[PDB]
């Protein structure tokens, strides 16, 4: 089996506080619902926000959400807050090696 | 929270080309061999180097190795090369949510 490639878009974006942020990831092969979205700030552990493509982890604000199943996935922050400024990554865990998208770095306009 | 906590050390280190580099990761509970080591450069997909604690992926040079089981793990670069400058993370995949160490940023000296 060839490694699963995750194509994540955009690589960077700028938006204003309150804005709706939309990030997509496409898997090169069908990974069912086995996708995680992580938030990563500089020098900190990547923090799991969503697992099983659409399930929110404990204590993660509900403005973070995921959808999709198979190959085409979408992550949304429905209102961007200052504390959400970070790089976000998708990761598939259908099959080792677990592989990541290239990341989307957010900044405030 | 019953999340598994990974304690990775050091948080940064400087070393010279050719030097041995040693990074450790402790899990808060027994995760058997379910530990991955990733290499991450700015603005790139984190790249899986070692899985099942000690197994290398394709194209990973022989200077990289991992060892350990249960709760204590070690990642070693036997002879640092320039292309090895990056932040390295451990990740347990025994149980969701998958959790990461705090990262080790490796610089030149």
Image: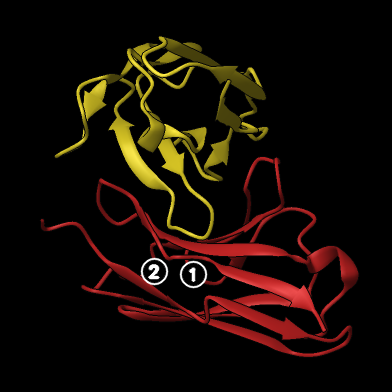
Chain colours: A yellow, B red
Disc 1 and disc 2 on one polypeptide chain: yes
- Residue B69 place in picture, x, y as percent: 38, 79
Residue displayed at 58% across by 20% down: A109
The chain under label 2 reads B
- Residue B27 place in picture, x, y as percent: 30, 73
Residue B29 visible in the displayed image? yes
Residue displayed at 52% across by 75% down: B11
- Circle on res. B33: 2
Asked whether the residues under the numbered discs 1 and 2 touch, taking CB atoms below 8 Å apart as contact, a structural biologist would say: yes
The local crowd at label 2, few if under 14, some if 14 to 19, many if 20 or more residues have their Cα within 10 Å, is many
**Which residue ends up furthest to the bottom in the rendered image?**
B19
Of residues B10 and B95, the one drawn nearer to the viewer in this rendering: B10
Give left or right: position of A107 versus B25: right
Of residues B94 and B12, the one drawn nearer to the viewer in this rendering: B12
- Circle on res. B53: 1
Residue displayed at 40% across by 9% down: A20
Give left or right: position of A79 versus A94: left
């Amino acid at each position: 089996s060839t490694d699963i490639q995750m194509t994540q878009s955009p690589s960077s974006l700028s938006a204003s506080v309150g804005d709706r942020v939309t990030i997509t990831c496409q898997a090169s092969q069908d990974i069912s619902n086995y996708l995680i979205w992580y938030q990563q700030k500089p020098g900190k552990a990547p923090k799991l926000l969503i697992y099983d493509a659409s399930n929110l982890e404990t204590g993660v604000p509900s403005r973070f959400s995921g959808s999709g199943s198979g190959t085409d996935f979408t992550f949304t922050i429905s209102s961007l807050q200052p504390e959400d400024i970070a790089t976000y990554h998708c990761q598939q865990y259908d099959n080792l090696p677990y592989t990541f998208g290239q990341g989307t770095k957010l900044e405030i306009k």
